[PDB]
Image (cartoon, rainbow over all chains, first blue to last red; front, side, top):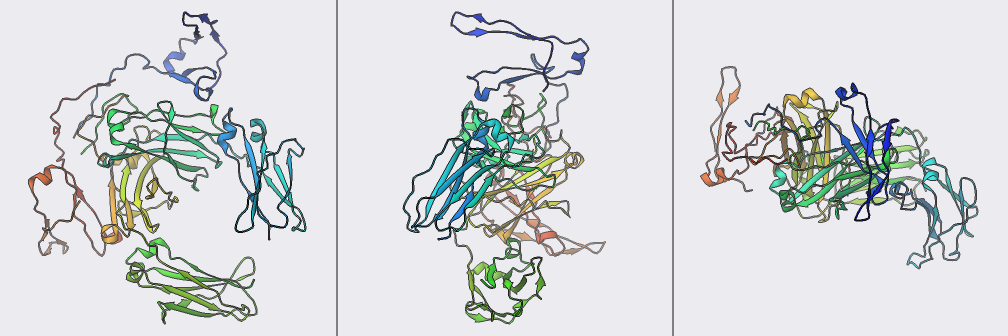
Length: 74
Length: 221
Length: 221
Length: 75
């Protein structure tokens, strides 16, 4: 929930369909990855509902594998 | 005939929504027949601003006229909590009547929103009830919506806020859905908008037997 | 204009309780100081009854005399729907004021009581919320209580019910417990008391392992 | 769903500690029991709170394997 000072935004690139895209890059120290701090990219636009769209980053950001332990049915 | 004045608080969703224009309405009832016209005066921040929305008078069997004065204020002005002043003068009334509206901004607490899995017995009934709990808010002005698949739900019930031991009110949102819709795995989102909320939006997704860990858990039976 | 006489309806808990007989109370407010004693008359279906009583006058903060009179009505009589009349006579009052009340009339339909187990994250917070809802009752005379292994502890939230689309009223009840209490798996009883229920009292039991359907529960959308 | 016509109850039997105990019996059809019908034995006593206690009985016996149907994984 706090702004990040060390972040960069790429200029938009024109597409064949006429839309635009860009990448927002955030750099952090290596030691910060162990704590698993939550990160998000916030974009302001009129098309999005209520001008809000947030995506959270966690450790299980890739393919998730279920935990080894399984609860007994009965 | 004993004119009366009533205070109507403004809807928080008008101020919270950027597109929606906030409006503050002061209403006067029991206007006597001999003086249908009511002298209305409006003040915002102690100053005069040139805007007015006076509803036309209507005839009633009780010889009572309802006059509503609507004022337009900005989001920042509404968030300030400054008093809005409505003065009403009538020939029958010996002295003018004064009313003011100003919501109290005290201890802004960020609301907490939770969703619960549907009850087991609910599968037997052909209607399934979905519950959305919200608490942790001091003021009574809360915006709630049911935004399923990006479109608002036709039917939703909101319980009035009630007192609590923690000092922050809590309430519920109830939705009724068909069993066929829930069987296929439909996802419904409970959106909460508050004046003290961050970015004025909180929502989450739910499904059948919601589980925070990525694991298949089953309790005793 | 002098004393005002009202007949407060009996509390819903006493009306439907077999052990606690319902009590009908009649209140006189703004009683003149020069005439503290007021003549009381209680009529049951036009019949005088000798079981009526009145409490001694109690001083109010506003220095206004307040008088209360209580009558013990039969528990079966309230089920039948008898008529009770309170009449108060005062020398200062020019004309006595009589208040008439009657039992609510409607089709008796059995309400449905459901229990919502907490989600997979509700125990992450310090307080775990247990919810029991009751739907489908036309009369407003209903009681909801919480029981925990024979130890009476009720939050008396008594959230006001709101009408549904079909007109069937519904209400919710919430209780707060600790992590250890929820993890223990002790039985928690939501007790509902209404006219339509069998024997006028029923209970619903909720445990940590409240129930798991035989069908597989998906952990992801 | 419907009150049961059948109802059997033995007279109370004195216990060693001085208390009492008894049983209540309900005979029904196999199909009704297999269909997961809701059954309970309401108990009313002077010492009991609210003078009403309900103990509903569920169809499941709590066996470790009762589903006997292969599960489906969806991510």
